[PDB]
Image: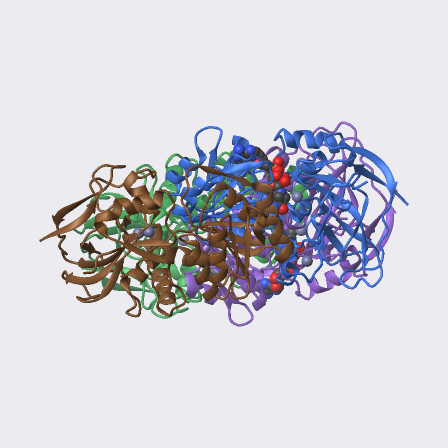
Chain colours: A blue, B brown, C purple, D green
């Protein structure tokens, strides 16, 4: 009837670990006993209110929560008790609007978002819509599979809308939580990978995961450096948390190329309209992934083409994590482990 | 042997109409007798030499020249004497690079541009690369058709890359020189047209052209109004690329929609990352088009679907024409008449 | 503190899944919480007690058990709690006898064997000697690395003792648990691989894994076939579970070749002395691998050169699994899943 | 032009001493005038033609012929007329194949064998390939050195391939024609020698030759006695390969040890898989040796470390010699003496 859970109550203030009531699945709902729970940079963005539309206080964050179905509301037909599932950013959608009908539920205006508009995986249990949960492969442990619930599907989908094809060069900008799995998805999709970040250790993580080439934007110029090394990229995926770089990216691509954007730092970035028009460049925002995207991203994980580099932490360690994530001191992803 | 031509000998200085030697077609080249020559703002930028890469002096502007093939060099098979052809912005391309081989010759690094990097149609005669000239429909007069070489293909290709389809909504931002042509192309492409400008006259014209909706941004926030009314436009064509138009386009576009930019404004534009990523927006640069694009845009004119607003002027009065353009006194397009 | 475990109580009898006391780490010992546990055919040999030296009844089998160190006895230095480790056939050696001093601890007459002379990994927990455990790479999941603890290390060392070198031919007889990863190690060691088995699906597996040539022993005499096809092999590794395969292997090598033996079916095989002597043939038994062998064989898996073909099963179904393995219905390895 | 020689004209029939022409050397060949000619059991099998591959009829046996170079063909530099040479089992090899290029001429597919596939030293003269003759030491009589061409190099190479080091234990199984020479080589090679036989006389000879330990398998189990006593032997040389000696060898040998087989018995021997594998035992066939092996074996005799037990007989009495051989009446080795 009661559960441990990390709750946000003030934008900018440390999360408190409290013992709140356990959510109960009504008709058409399910309950999930959380086994592991990934920490996304989005969680930071939320807890501080970096965004135009802010979460409602108080709430439990976490949209990379994974575990077992521990209760099944009325008439649930897609999942049964004991099912291995995850609860991603896209908590639910309406299912019949133009977006939803075209398989673009990620754009649904009636969508609810896990760990934001509704409570998420930073708790021992969480109620979910069984129609939008990720169905997890048994062969991958909860801790390893957790980051795929967002970092994975996001960059998988991001790479898809770069409109690049096998044999072509793609640039991953920002080799962090999203970045480091993006390199892996790219290679599995037959692409050649170039990497850029501000820390040489993150570039080395990239090189190990498959990237053929890397650059430190802090050193010399990333764009210019890339035009010389590979003759510009066919595509670019931006997972960086800095507005600048959202600008340097437009210069790393060859004419007719496409830059896909995953990062969500507040503010604008400078777009050279003249060159964009003259070089026929495409800039494209990519928001997480649909249910099919998610299932496919999970499939890559299942086959071992993608393995997330994760650090373990305890629910109680929540705030220590946030700090180091802000400090850019995290290698890959941090995952809260509930295994008591 | 000798011909009259408008010549730029010093950037910024009023053109002088000089008697100059009629250019002769060598092997693989043809000669064209100009009957009409389109004028547009691009010609101002070539004359002022105010773009990042300047024309070489001296030179003859004009990339909307049309007339008859009056002489054919050796090894030419695409056209013959008497053929009615146009010499558009894309004078030539290398034909072997990645872009050229993939049908994107407009992105060719080695391309030459009529009335900019080589002499153009502000003269009685012009030499052209037969592989890159436009094949004019007999159905349409020289004056009427000239603007289609530039304004026509630009907005047409711009509409194509909005990845919209018949039945869907498109916003035509700016109903001026390009805009009033874009409306007609949009209608012929089965699109529902929403017209946006600040000029009541231009909006009335848009309505007369078949625009289903017309919003004056002076009195009404088009972004807010369109979202409320139609949930946004699947596609947005920005024919007048000001920061205000760019920002508003991002506000007007439906989630997952596409914005095509037809202009070449100076400076960096501020681009809101959050909106672009969350809304899954595509931003795409597009000016003029490939040889295929041009032929297709020409066919719409031939079939009576598209008719440019045009007035004529004499070669001797081009400086006055440049005057009207700079002061924005031109409704539609001005076309130099070379016919006797 | 109790735990589930598959126990052999009588030779030839079905194993029973009993509740048994959790083994505690004495001084110099550590406790391992099993996450996965590979099923080796040696386990069937033990449960049936068909070797001259029987295991003591009762006993828990399993020498491919992997997991996290869950407890540390006094005086342990080699590893710490949380460490990823595996417990191989060679549970421990005396450390100071002639064999141990020369790095051949696999020959120690005072050695203990996991899942044979001491309890193994068919249980939730296993106590182990930290000086002899496998130190697992983070890169590889428990399910996939499990077969390396014996299947991998055994055939890797076996291939080493064939005295073959890069470019030369090696034959793998019996493409089962050991055989199918042997093919992979062979390739990683620069050898050309030939495959022999009595099942087409097995040989198709070998072909997928890099076998340059393959032949079904049931369809033709494999010795004659290989002599004709590749001119005889420089080396053979025998991992088959039938004595006939041992006899046939001796005829597969070219003069001066080496046959290494991993397989352990009961009984004798026919050694043609005359030919062995005249042709200067070497026949060599190879028993699992040393700690050095194990570490190196693990490195090959971490780098992606070797990936075990694995299907998971539950502790409860260990008897059905033994059955399928007995009748040769398993493709690759079966690994018991102990994860949450 | 004619000479006397013992000739096999029908398999199994008694040999006849016939008058045949002296074989004359052509280019690259030399002629040897026999002073002594060793006899062994291989000569019996040649005369009986009971081996898988038979001699061609008719032919003169003898692969242990020693004497002076009495004539040379053109292009001979390794030896000159007057040189004391022996004509061993390996008459010649192609010199180009994979085996020959690797110093393993004994494995050459196109090899010819003296007194088997080509005429041998059972005659007054014999033609040889100077590139393959043994170069005899000045200080050892012909009669005494003859057996080294076969028995000598056989047990020497045999001992070498056991891969035993000075100081280590080696078992000489069977102290007969080969065994009694093997004991001496083993001691010269710094090995500790354990002798095994079922004959007290032979075992007493072993002790006389430096055998540190002697055990009669008739009275006591040599395997048990040796494992208990010295911990098993690092190496075992089986010079009389019966199934018994073979199986006892597997028992006597230390774990990771090597068993070398010198005999050529018929049929397949039952080989215990469990023992060979678990003990990490090497079983290796070895008879005669390479040209370097032979020169090395000859050096030992020259230095007085090895002296064969020899009894002389006349050419005319070869049939009687074959008789005593067949009846196992020969102590040591019998050598035909062609001296004045
Ligand atoms: N569209 C989507 O749904 C998608 C999905 C979740 C991630 N988000 C966002 O994506 C961003 C990244 O996600 P994350 O969890 O991996 O954050 P992260 O902290 O794990 O990784 C960020 C990386 O960006 C790097 N970086 C910072 N400045 C840089 C620069 N100037 N150039 C290059 N690299 C730079 C850091 O080194 C770090 O490696 C976050 O803003 C997050 O909110 C959106
Ligand atoms: N000496 C050691 O170091 C080594 C290590 C452990 C494994 N063993 C033994 O190795 C053997 C194999 O292990 P496993 O787990 O891979 O068993 P397995 O059942 O997985 O594989 C056995 C394979 O042998 C094949 N086979 C059967 N008859 C054959 C024939 N006549 N010719 C060719 N192939 C034939 C089967 O098709 C099968 O593919 C077992 O006996 C096991 O006990 C010893
Ligand atoms: Zn996220
Ligand atoms: Zn919807
Ligand atoms: Zn123009
Ligand atoms: Zn080109
Ligand atoms: Zn095993
Ligand atoms: Zn030991
Ligand atoms: Zn002999
Ligand atoms: Zn040869």
Residue A148 seen in render = yes
**Quadrant of the displayed image that contains ligand 10:** bottom left
Name the one closer to the observer, B3 or D260.
B3
Please determine whether, in this image, residue A235 is positioned above or below residue D50.
above
Residue located 82% across and 63% down the image = A75
> Where residue C194 appears, x then y in whole percent?
49, 59
Across and down, in percent, residue A198 comes to 52, 31
In terms of depth relative to the viewer, which is nearer, D192 or A216? Answer: A216
Quarter of the picture holding the N terminus of chain C:
top right
- Residue displayed at 48% across by 32% down: A217
In the displayed image of the protein, which residue is found farthest to the left?
B1
As drawn, is A30 to the left or to the right of D93? Answer: right
Counting labels gives: 0
- Residue A160 position, x and y percent, is 53, 53
Residue drawn at 41 percent across, 58 percent down: B181
Place of residue B274 in the rendered image (x, y in percent of width and height, measured from the top left): 60, 42
Quarter residue D226 falls in: top right
* Residue C162 can be seen, yes or no: no
Q: Residue furthest right?
A: A1
């Amino acid at each position: 009837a009661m559960m441990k859970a990390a709750v946000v109550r003030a934008f900018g203030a440390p999360l408190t670990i409290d013992e709140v009531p356990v959510p109960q699945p009504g008709p058409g709902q399910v309950q999930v006993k959380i086994e592991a729970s990934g920490v996304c940079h989005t969680d930071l963005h939320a807890a501080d209110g970096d965004w135009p539309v802010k979460p409602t206080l108080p709430f439990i964050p976490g949209h990379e929560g994974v575990g077992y179905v521990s209760a099944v509301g009325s008439g649930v037909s897609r999942v049964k008790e004991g099912d291995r599932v995850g609860v991603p950013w896209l908590y639910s959608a309406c299912g019949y609007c133009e977006h939803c009908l075209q398989g673009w539920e990620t754009l649904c205006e009636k969508q609810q978002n896990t760990g934001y508009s509704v409570n998420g995986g930073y708790g021992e249990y969480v109620v979910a819509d069984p129609n939008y949960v990720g169905l997890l492969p048994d062969k991958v442990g909860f801790v390893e599979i957790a980051p795929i619930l967002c970092a994975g599907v996001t960059v998988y989908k991001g790479l898809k809308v770069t409109d690049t094809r096998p044999g072509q060069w793609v640039v991953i900008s920002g080799i962090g939580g999203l970045g480091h799995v993006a390199v892996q998805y790219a290679r599995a999709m037959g692409l050649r990978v170039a990497a850029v970040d501000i820390d040489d250790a993150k570039l080395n993580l990239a090189r190990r995961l498959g990237a053929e080439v890397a650059v430190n934007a802090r050193d010399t110029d990333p764009a210019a450096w890339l035009q010389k090394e590979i003759g510009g990229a066919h595509g670019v995926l931006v997972t960086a948390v800095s507005p600048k770089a959202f600008s340097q990216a437009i210069g790393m691509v060859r004419r007719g190329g496409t830059i896909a954007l995953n990062g969500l730092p507040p503010g604008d970035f400078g777009t050279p309209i003249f060159d964009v028009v003259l070089k026929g460049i495409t800039i494209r925002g990519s928001i997480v992934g649909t249910r099919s995207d998610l299932q496919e991203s999970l499939d890559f994980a299942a086959h071992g083409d993608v393995k997330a580099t994760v650090s373990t932490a305890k629910l109680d360690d929540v705030n220590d994590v946030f700090g180091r994530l802000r400090e850019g001191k995290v290698e890959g992803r941090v995952v809260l482990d509930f295994s008591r």
